[PDB]
């Protein structure tokens, strides 16, 4: 995003306008807790491709 | 609980109880046979068409 205006509520611009789409779907890129052979396996790692 | 037993097992904590693992397995054999002089009194009927 582009930042806009004062920086004070810029965190608050992020928290309120995103909260519906942020809290609903799980993020892809937290896969660090996935193990080594739990990476390449097809179960739970449809993000393989 | 079975919801909790994801986060114990998929992450890698041993959940306090351990398993025995049963599979089936199948093997071809090559069986030798034997018999004595007369084991089967055998019979043959008349053909019909």
Image (cartoon, coloured by chain):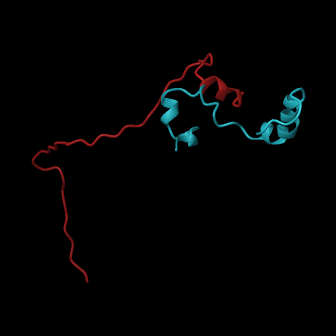
Chain colours: A cyan, B red
Q: In the visual, does A41 lie left or right of A25?
A: left
Q: Against B14, is B42 above or below?
A: below
- Of the 4 image quadrants, the one containing the N terminus of chain B is top right
Q: In the visual, does B6 lie left or right of B39?
A: right
The image quadrant that residue A10 belongs to is top right
* Numbered circles on residues, count: 0
Given the current orientation, which residue lies at the most extreme front position? A5
The image quadrant that residue A3 belongs to is top right
Residue B21 position, x and y percent, is 48, 28
Q: Against A32, is B47 above or below?
A: below
The image quadrant that residue A17 belongs to is top right
Residue B49 position, x and y percent, is 26, 83
User: B8 or A12, which lies in front?
Assistant: A12
Residue plotted at (62% across, 16% down): B16
User: A45 or B32, which lies in front?
Assistant: A45
Residue A42 position, x and y percent, is 52, 41
Given the current orientation, which residue lies at the most extreme top position? B16
Q: In the visual, does A34 lie left or right of A25?
A: left
Residue plotted at (52% across, 33% down): A39
Given the current orientation, which residue lies at the most extreme bottom position? B49
Residue plotted at (48% across, 29% down): A37
User: A49 or B47, which lies in front?
Assistant: A49
User: B32 or B13, which lies in front?
Assistant: B13
Q: In the visual, does B19 lie left or right of B33?
A: right
């Amino acid at each position: 995003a582009a930042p806009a205006g004062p920086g004070a509520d810029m965190q608050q611009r992020f928290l309120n306008a995103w909260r519906q789409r942020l809290a609903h779907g799980r993020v892809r890129w937290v896969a660090e807790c996935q193990m080594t052979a739990e990476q390449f396996m097809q179960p739970d790692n449809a993000n393989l491709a | 609980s079975p919801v909790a037993l994801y986060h114990q097992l998929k992450t890698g904590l041993h959940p306090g109880f351990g398993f025995t693992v049963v599979r089936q397995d199948r093997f071809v054999t090559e069986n030798v046979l034997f018999s004595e002089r007369a084991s089967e009194a055998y019979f043959l009927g008349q053909l019909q068409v």
